[PDB]
Amino acid sequence: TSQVRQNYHQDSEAAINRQINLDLYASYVYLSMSYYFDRDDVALKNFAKYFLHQSHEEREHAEKLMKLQNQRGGRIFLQDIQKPDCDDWESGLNAMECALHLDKNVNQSLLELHKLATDKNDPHLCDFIETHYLNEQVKAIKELGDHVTNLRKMGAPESGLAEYLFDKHTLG
Amino acid sequence: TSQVRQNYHQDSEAAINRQINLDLYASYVYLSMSYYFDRDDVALKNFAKYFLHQSHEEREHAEKLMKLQNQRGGRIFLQDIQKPDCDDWESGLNAMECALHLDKNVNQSLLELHKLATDKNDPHLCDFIETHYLNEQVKAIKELGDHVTNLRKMGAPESGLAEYLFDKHTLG
Amino acid sequence: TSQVRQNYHQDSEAAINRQINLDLYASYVYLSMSYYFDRDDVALKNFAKYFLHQSHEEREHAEKLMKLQNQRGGRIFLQDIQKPDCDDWESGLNAMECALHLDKNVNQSLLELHKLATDKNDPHLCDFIETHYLNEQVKAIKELGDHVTNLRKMGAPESGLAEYLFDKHTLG
Amino acid sequence: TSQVRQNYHQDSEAAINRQINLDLYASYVYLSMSYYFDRDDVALKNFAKYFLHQSHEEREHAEKLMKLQNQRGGRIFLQDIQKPDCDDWESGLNAMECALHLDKNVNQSLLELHKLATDKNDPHLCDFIETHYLNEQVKAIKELGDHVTNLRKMGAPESGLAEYLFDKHTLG
Amino acid sequence: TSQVRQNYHQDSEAAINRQINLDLYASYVYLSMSYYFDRDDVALKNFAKYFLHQSHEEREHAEKLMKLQNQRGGRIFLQDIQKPDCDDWESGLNAMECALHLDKNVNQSLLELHKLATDKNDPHLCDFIETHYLNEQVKAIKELGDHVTNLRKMGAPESGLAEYLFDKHTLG
Amino acid sequence: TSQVRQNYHQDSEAAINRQINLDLYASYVYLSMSYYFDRDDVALKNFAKYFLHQSHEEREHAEKLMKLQNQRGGRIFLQDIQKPDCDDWESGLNAMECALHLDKNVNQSLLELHKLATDKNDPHLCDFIETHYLNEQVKAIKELGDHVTNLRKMGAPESGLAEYLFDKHTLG
Ligand SMILES: [Ca+2]
Ligand SMILES: [Ca+2]
Ligand SMILES: [Ca+2]
Ligand SMILES: [Ca+2]
Ligand SMILES: [Ca+2]
Ligand SMILES: [Ca+2]
Ligand SMILES: [Ca+2]
Ligand SMILES: [Ca+2]
Ligand SMILES: [Ca+2]
Ligand SMILES: [Ca+2]
Ligand SMILES: [Ca+2]
Ligand SMILES: [Ca+2]
Ligand SMILES: [Ca+2]
Ligand SMILES: [Ca+2]
């Protein structure tokens, strides 16, 4: 038992390790998406930039959890970071839809983590999740929803013009 | 009778109170429109910004009338601010058409108020209305007309691309 | 169901709509109070300024809730904004006492909203209310209490001198 | 009953008074430690500076609680501030170990206070404790743990060289 | 016997420890007074600020004595800091009268300490007391006398207006 | 076949994909090491900082290869990023020794990649590897060798003092 450990349940420690992996996985998905848009036969530089930014953001979230783990006297246990489900992401719209799905899954995990912290009467962990993650996640989801709506209304994915103009005017 | 009151007819005092309510109502309509465009399934941020600006402008007009009421020794009597006729505003074009209709109704009220002030030989009130409101209203109406014309010519509301591009290039 | 919606109960959505209306109502009360102090037979410019500031603050609170509603995939439904209970607010002390009563009623609503969010296991909504509203409300109430105490100790409302000096030295 | 009081349980009011005393006590412990390191036969100026900083921090925490008490309409009741358990703190390592023990006891009190606020459905008080104290306390504990680890690994307390070098390189 | 100790009598060492406690006690009294004026039913912010400043000043005096103790090779022995005699300080005038009484008691202790240092032929200690404390104390007493006089002449404590105006114009 | 593809062998494309994975793996190893040194029972902040820097560097190398893949008309295929071989890295020296081993393995892969590019007469790929990676890798290896030597000479890992001082004076 760590000399710093206090009011930190074994289950919370484990759930934090799972959340670290999930955040790294989400970083990897966004990395994959980014470089798809960098392909010469896709060539949407601002979609590429957008998802690369998301990738780095997820990695930062992971690192903050690793810091939290140590702050509470828990022990970090890393797992394989799974390759994303797709190598080819189809279109800007499809990638945005996939990102929305991903962010809602990450949000579900955050909510379960918060439920667990609540059940274990760990107000420090509840506060940590609220402070750093819950509103961040709601904002991300809202933004992805907004992007999906605009792309659909513009005529994506069939309109390559729509995805081109969205790349310039929203993502650029 | 207020110690400051002079040449200020009871009817004018009452019409000013009605105009205060109408301006607050118009503020509320524009507030409603603004946040419609903030919905994730509408997502036109510059339409949202445009109508929020209009909302605050109408509130300022109301406050200036409340100040006028007191300046002349009249007494402010507030009424309920009615909820707008619509919760869902359909499209950017439809909202602009609705705003045009609203601004012309407010203009009609201003003109009737000016007629009343003229009939009561209240040149201070005539001047107040001319100075702060009549040209402001003509400019607003002209701008809304311009916006409606462009949206129609671009292919709104059926073209989601048209409303997207107008949001970026005119309202942004 | 909104593409962004997640862990957001129907009851919470409805309570948010009620809170939007209550905040707009509170904005309206403070607007009414402000311009009472602008009357030539009251003439306390800093009481006027104080309540106008409060009015704009309540409107901002309302707008932030409208933003929250959309962020979570809820749908804004606006209602009439009721006229305040008084047209004449009597004295600076009486208005401050009325403001205290109002702020405690708004606080009660916030607390019920937080209870509802807690009951529906919505930590994002709990956090939103805590972050933006609960401490703001406690500070407001404390300040109004302070003002009431000073006005009473100075001899308000019978001492017009007391209300004059408080206007200058506390509110100015 | 205070005119500002709302949703503030008698038990919470009392627990806040106990927490004020505990924070003042912790301020006193750290004051005692600081000046031990100022002795000519101890002479570790940066250990002295470190604990004096901690002392002032605990006093600030106490004052913020006194402010909270009044904000909520509670009434501050002060108690004797007990002298620390030791006059002589032995060594830098021993003092750090004692500080760790102290901070974990203060943390336990904070957690019990948060449990009480949770049980009394006082989300404002929960938020206050989370905002100002829980993460602050976790950071403090982590830092003290870090210091203890380094001092032990360096060969303290038997190595006067170790405590000298830690004073220079970590605390200086 | 400390390697630095020279011409420092056991009795002086002990009297310095008593003076440290008295200064901490005076810090505590002023802390208590400060937050009384922070209550919503007292609400004199500049009385609050004034006494908080005094509190910090007394703590600084205590710390300087702790430094002196070590400088001379004496050993600091801390005692409980007694809670102040009052929880409720009644009025601004009453608190000022209480502060005057306190400062004169502290002054009496300083004078006895100086007598002791004189009797033990300790010119360094005599000089320390003269330099840091005797004139400081005379100035404090004079200022408190001045404040009491003005408050009485203005009609305090019965005039809440008097205490309000003194808070603004002397303490603000 | 990509419209940009020219003189880019299938085998090279595949080896680039393997190198991307290896770089991501090396990023993960260094991430793991970094946060080990962040543990409260290890507490070497500059070892932590050093390895975190290395982690980000490896990720950048990976991203540059992903860019290269697309530049040449190859197709990125991502694989699982394997968890590092250790969860606990023992000591600063042991981690440095492990980093040296890792960097030499990465170097071996780079050299094989360069051999492959040479065998396939791909001077652009040879130049890319030389420009961005070969000298970078030699410098990294040299630095890690230097660090290992100093740690050993200082008496690590048995001397916790040695690792403490190296953390301060070399890594800080
Ligand atoms: Ca994101
Ligand atoms: Ca796999
Ligand atoms: Ca307008
Ligand atoms: Ca109605
Ligand atoms: Ca307010
Ligand atoms: Ca009504
Ligand atoms: Ca501390
Ligand atoms: Ca005792
Ligand atoms: Ca919270
Ligand atoms: Ca003083
Ligand atoms: Ca006692
Ligand atoms: Ca490197
Ligand atoms: Ca594996
Ligand atoms: Ca070359």
Image: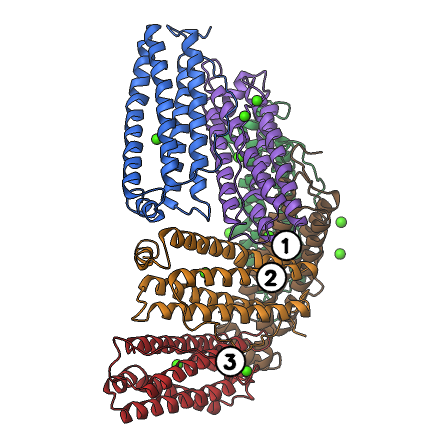
Chain colours: A brown, B red, C orange, D purple, E blue, F green
Q: Please report whichever mark, 2 or 1, sits nearer to the chain's N-terminal start.
A: 1
The residue carrying mark 2 is: F69
Do callouts 2 and 1 mark residues in contact (Cβ within 8 Å)? yes
Residue C53 can be seen, yes or no: yes
Q: Say what secondary structure mark 3 lies in.
A: helix
Using residue B147 as the reference point, say whether residue C160 is left or right of it: left
Q: In which quarter of the view is residue E111 placed?
A: top left
Kindly identify which chain the residue marked by label 2 belongs to: F
Q: What is the spatial separation of the Cα atoms under label 2 and label 3, in whole angstroms?
A: 35 Å
Q: Which mark is residue B164?
A: 3
Are tags 2 and 3 found on a single chain? no
Nearer to us: label 1 or label 3: 3
From the viewer's perspective, is residue C90 above or below residue A27?
Answer: below
Q: Position of residue F38 (x, y in %)?
A: 60, 38
Chain identity of mark 3? B
Left or right, C22 with respect to E144, comes to right
Left or right of B141 on screen, residue F141 = right
How many angstroms separate mark 1 from mark 3 (CA)?
Answer: 39 Å
The reply to whether callout 2 and callout 3 are in contact (CB within 8 Å) is no
Q: Is mark 3 within 8 Å of ligand 1?
A: no
Give me the disc on residue F20: 1
Q: Amino acid at mark 1?
A: Ile
